[PDB]
Length: 9
Ligand SMILES: *C(=O)c1ccc(-c2ccc(C(=O)OCC)cn2)nc1
Ligand SMILES: *NNC(=O)c1ccc(-c2ccc(C(N)=O)cn2)nc1
Ligand SMILES: CCc1ccccc1
Ligand SMILES: Cc1ccc(C)cc1
Image 1 (tube, rainbow, N blue to C red):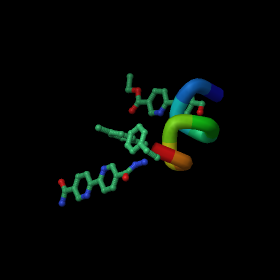
Image 2: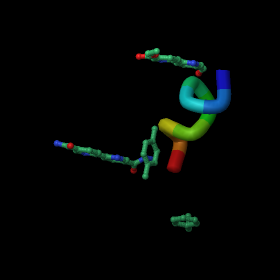
Image 3: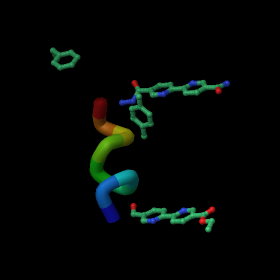
């Protein structure tokens, strides 16, 4: 989940 968001950055 963290990675799913972190792709934005
Ligand atoms: C949420 O974005 C997210 C994405 C990916 C993963 C994740 C966890 C573990 C592995 C892995 O290769 O584990 C080897 C033990 C890969 N990706 N977790 C949360
Ligand atoms: N928000 N995330 C990024 O901007 C981001 C872009 C690209 C990468 C990345 C990581 C690792 C490789 C590689 N070939 O090992 C390439 N690009 N990370 C984050
Ligand atoms: C969008 C500005 C920025 C860039 C990279 C990381 C954080 C913030
Ligand atoms: C999804 C992601 C992976 C690595 C960095 C450094 C940033 C984002």
